[PDB]
């Protein structure tokens, strides 16, 4: 319906490691770290912890979850 309200958009990519999740060049975040506050909350609903704070401003952003559990950050 109604649209065309802005050009730029809030997009980001967060990968999920065995027990940690990353996001863009940023380093790997700890599922229990701080940034995981909006990541776990937003990523769970569908928003990025950083790019959403820039545009979303609460917890709403389009992110791409990279599938790499048994292939990335193998804690075990």
Image (cartoon, rainbow, N blue to C red):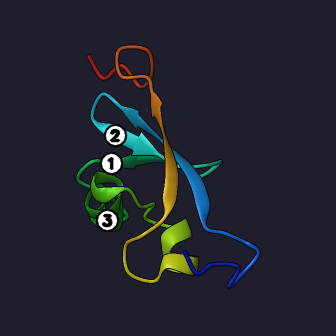
Q: Which residue is mark 1?
A: 30
Label 1: how many residues lie within 10 Å, few (<14), some (14-19) or many (20+)? some
Image quadrant of residue 45? Answer: bottom left
Q: Which residue is mark 3?
A: 34
Image quadrant of residue 21? Answer: top left
Question: In what quadrant of the picture does the N terminus appear?
Answer: bottom right
Q: Secondary structure at mark 3?
A: loop
Label 2: how many residues lie within 10 Å, few (<14), some (14-19) or many (20+)? some
Q: Is 37 located above or below residue 2 in the figure?
A: above
Query: What residue appears at the point 35 percent right and 22 percent down from the top-left corner?
Result: 69
Q: Is 59 located above or below residue 20 in the figure?
A: below
Query: What residue appears at the point 61 percent right and 59 percent down from the top-left corner?
Result: 11
Q: Seen in the image, is 29 located left or right of residue 55?
A: left
**Residue 35, horizontal then vertical, whole percent:** 37, 64
Which of disc 2 and disc 3 is earlier in sequence?
A: 2
Question: In what quadrant of the picture does the C terminus appear?
Answer: top left
Q: Seen in the image, is 33 located left or right of residue 25?
A: left
**Residue 39, horizontal then vertical, whole percent:** 35, 59
Are the residues flagged by discs 2 and 1 in contact, CB closer than 8 Å?
Answer: yes
Q: Which residue is mark 2?
A: 20
**Residue 43, horizontal then vertical, whole percent:** 35, 54
């Amino acid at each position: 319906e109604r649209r065309r309200h802005s050009g730029q958009d809030v997009h980001v990519v967060l990968k999920l490691w065995k027990t940690g999740f990353s996001l863009d060049n940023g380093d790997l975040r700890s599922y229990q770290d701080p940034s995981n506050a909006q990541f776990l909350e937003s990523i769970r609903r569908g928003e990025v912890p950083a790019e959403l704070r820039r545009l979303a401003h609460g917890g709403q952003v389009n992110l791409d979850m990279e599938d790499h559990r048994d292939e990335d950050f193998v804690k075990p």
